[PDB]
Amino acid sequence: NKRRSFYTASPSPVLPGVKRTA
Amino acid sequence: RSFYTASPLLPVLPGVKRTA
Amino acid sequence: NNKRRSFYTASPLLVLPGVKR
Amino acid sequence: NNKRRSFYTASPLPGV
Amino acid sequence: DIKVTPGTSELVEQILALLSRYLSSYIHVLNKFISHLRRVATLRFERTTLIKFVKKLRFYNDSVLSYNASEFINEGKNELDPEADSFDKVILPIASMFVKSVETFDLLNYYLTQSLQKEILSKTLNEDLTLTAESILAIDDTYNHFVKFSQWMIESLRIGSNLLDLEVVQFAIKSADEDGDNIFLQEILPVNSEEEFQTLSAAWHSILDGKLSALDEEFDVVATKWHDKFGKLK
Amino acid sequence: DIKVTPGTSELVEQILALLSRYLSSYIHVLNKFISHLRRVATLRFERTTLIKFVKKLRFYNDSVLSYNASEFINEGKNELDPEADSFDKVILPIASMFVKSVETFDLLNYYLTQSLQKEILSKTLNEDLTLTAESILAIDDTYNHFVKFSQWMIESLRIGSNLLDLEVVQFAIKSADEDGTNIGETDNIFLQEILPVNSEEEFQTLSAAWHSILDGKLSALDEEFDVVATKWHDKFGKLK
Amino acid sequence: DIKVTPGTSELVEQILALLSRYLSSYIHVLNKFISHLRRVATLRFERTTLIKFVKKLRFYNDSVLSYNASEFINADSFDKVILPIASMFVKSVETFDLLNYYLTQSLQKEILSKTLNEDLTLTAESILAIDDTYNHFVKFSQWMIESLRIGSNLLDLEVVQFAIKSADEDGDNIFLQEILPVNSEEEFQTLSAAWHSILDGKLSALDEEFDVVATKWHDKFGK
Amino acid sequence: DIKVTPGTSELVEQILALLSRYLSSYIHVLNKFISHLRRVATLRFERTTLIKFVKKLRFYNDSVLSYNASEFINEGKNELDPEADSFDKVILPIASMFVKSVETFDLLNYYLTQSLQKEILSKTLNEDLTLTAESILAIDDTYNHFVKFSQWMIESLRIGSNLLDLEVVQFAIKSADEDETDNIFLQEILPVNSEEEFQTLSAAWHSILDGKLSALDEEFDVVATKWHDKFG
RNA sequence: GAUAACUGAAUCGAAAGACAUUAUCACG
RNA sequence: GAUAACUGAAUCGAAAGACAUUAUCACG
Ligand SMILES: [Mg+2]
Ligand SMILES: [Mg+2]
Ligand SMILES: [Mg+2]
Ligand SMILES: [Mg+2]
């Protein structure tokens, strides 16, 4: 969570070809 | 922009004229 | 302690006219 | 001038 | 081996156009910001850092806009030819461009939305040239989706390797192994025809255009904020 | 010329009580701020600077509260007594204390309301422990009036010299000479003329009118220090 | 046309090892710098920027070190096999470009502005080395790509196109010199190993200079 | 009971000249430091704090230099009358100036030699911008002796009160209560009975303090040279 | 005096226009 | 691991109480 803030500065649609619960 | 006050923009006082 | 004394001087440190030990 | 070139370097062969 | 069609050329061009739109949104807002920053003496070197970044984005954009896809695709004749290109071979360098770009945006977004934001407040003692919270949200949302689209293209055609892995995707995976829903961890279904890739691609296209419009809208709001709070006269 | 009365002792004590109230307002709010600042690592040394200041104020306050005025005023016996003290001689060290205090407040206010305010924003990236604009206004308004009251005491009895001059008063004067603002009725409090006083009865009357005004300013100051202490509580002290 | 051999697997692994050495040199010196910077309050956010960069380099390094070349080679064209290696180089090189500007230019100026403390700056010689190594990895990258005629608009390096567009407008420079095509894999291998020798030479000079700066940072701050 | 002479005027002027020398040493070295600091972006507000202090010293210095002592000393219808001024009355505002100045130096020294020194290392890690240990020693040694001289003037003529007490002197005393002496502040001031005696002791103090201010100057010159060589 | 120079194409200006022949900063 | 120590009397806690046997911070 101090490591996770180097990958996004932010603290539910289907996306094509992405199986939803996985 | 002052060393003398942080409020630039600042009724009759005992023993004082209104005059310089 | 010496934090109280550090407000009065920056030193280890502590003959003179009008003065008698 | 050298301000354009300064974005590409901080400075003043085989198969070539 | 899934095979090329005459319609393949335009599918590539359409994918690359998204990338160009993503790059161009940043270049426009950054050009503005860089101009405003010229008037702030204490942000002189941060400004030069931004110029370096924007130049890189601009170059990727010229590269993408000058790429003639047809010049790199051997095409279908009707269907039979064993010297015509694999769809694999054709998507690979497109995907690879996306990866390079996405990793560049990662570096930039951290600088732009985190470090520099803090530095701006520290140095100037105000909010007049910070980004809006909503613009940061949009930036991250757009990034996330382009990362996921990039992963879809690569994993759907099973053309991935250690070298095409995105840092943020591996990080999410390694974090889930150590820890016991997250967009990056969801599974990519393989695709078997080009007709299927095309269909899913155009659905992605619609989603990503949606994200880029939201991004554009938020970049317009901040450019206005910068105008009202810093640029204009007093 | 002007001579002491038995009532002079209490007039001094009353003047000194204002100074003590001024000092004590600062000491209270600064004690709170210093406590809050203990929890901010990046403001560690600024905190020690404030402690150094607050200690100085506290010392001036103990000094003032312990001063027994009667022990330094030789009253007269039935009226005339050629050994009884001049009113001049008696007000002089009181005025002189005010000057020392006022110049201390000047140094502190600049640090507290300007430098440190900027530093707090630079270091913490928020407003949670800055002062309110209104508290700053009050600080400056109170300072201005204590400066003017100090000048009144000194110039009214003609007991001034180069050494009792207040920096802010001379600055206003030198600024008007150079600019040309000393012509006519000025709106600037520091440039307005002090009328001399001729009796102690007159000094007492004017003194008590000043007393009323200054108590008014110190209540406004206290009110604003209560608001900012609350602000510091709500925005920083209280965790979730 | 040109075809793989059983020896191709090791040629790829050897090329990738250079990239790993280049990445690792930076990661080591940056880890040290980031630690020293902990003690400078005014450089707190510049430090976090460097962490972001170093994480990226570290990731490229794990990626490269985990890549088993044989798992991706068969029969395959030599073209097809070099392409993703070249492509990794390009991604890395453009990352280094961004990082070098920050590290050697912006940040250097910022350090002096904020601290006036030249103990925190890089040495001139380390900067020279950085730029010399970059230039040669750029040129090696271009060689691999243009020699096998596998290039495109998308594999163009910013610095190479900038040099070219600058010569057109202006009317000797390493980036503008011509890449000769290669016709056999035996020829690529020969030239590759000659490049390998040169680049190892540059990386040792780089390591030497990173040692010197790290020593300075140790002596002038230390543990 | 203790009266002015025609020589009193010059004794005051001489005392004040020391204070001016003390103020001026600081003003000189601070002017230099404030200039060097102009090139360090992270010390921008500390710099403005120093300016505020140096302005205050500069004002005390102009005040002292422009004070004409004779304009405030009634020598009298020469050496006769109860109209002529008490020596008490004349020294009092001089002593009082010393006290104001000494308490200003106390505030400044803490900032300059302690807080700001730590802040400089925290922000820059650049010891080129710090004071030398020897300059700090000198600063504190000079302060101590001006504090003691100030106390001597006040207690020797028995003109002291709660309002002229120096914070550092009371602190020493309260610390000894809670705890013959080696501590300068606790040692006893002998009363003086003539002006001739005050004058004699005053000039001996004058010699000692000039000695401290030269050592101070010397150390301010060393640190200024360092600042010149390493930046300027 | 110092600082600020991506052919970048933005920025500032209602406009005319401005943009190193410029702009900003600086202890009364 | 690092950082924080005015006998100051505030601060935190509804309270009991807590307050270097503590608190805060961290690619760490
Ligand atoms: Mg920078
Ligand atoms: Mg400080
Ligand atoms: Mg400060
Ligand atoms: Mg930064």
Image (cartoon, coloured by chain):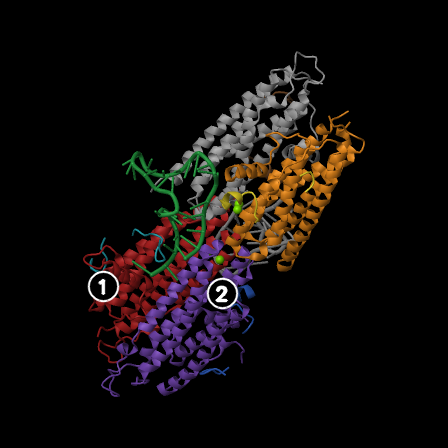
Chain colours: A brown, B cyan, C blue, D yellow, F red, G orange, H purple, I green
x, y percent for residue H133: 55, 68
x, y percent for residue G163: 56, 39
Along the viewing direction, whichever of D6 and G114 lies nearer the viewer: D6
x, y percent for residue F151: 28, 64
Comparing labels 1 and 2, the label whose residue is closer to the camera? 2
Kindly identify which numbered label has been placed on residue F194: 1
* Residue F158 location, quadrant: bottom left
* Residue A11 location, quadrant: top right
| Badge 2 amino acid | His
Q: Is residue G186 left or right of residue H161?
A: right
* Residue named by callout 2: H228
Classed neighbour count for the residue bearing mark 1: other residues with Cα under 10 Å, few (<14), some (14–19), many (≥20): many
Q: Is residue F38 left or right of residue H65?
A: right
Q: Is residue F4 left or right of residue H231?
A: left
Q: Which residue is outermost to the front?
A: G171
- Which residue does the image show at 32% across and 54% down from the upper left? F141
Along the viewing direction, whichever of H110 and G182 lies nearer the viewer: G182
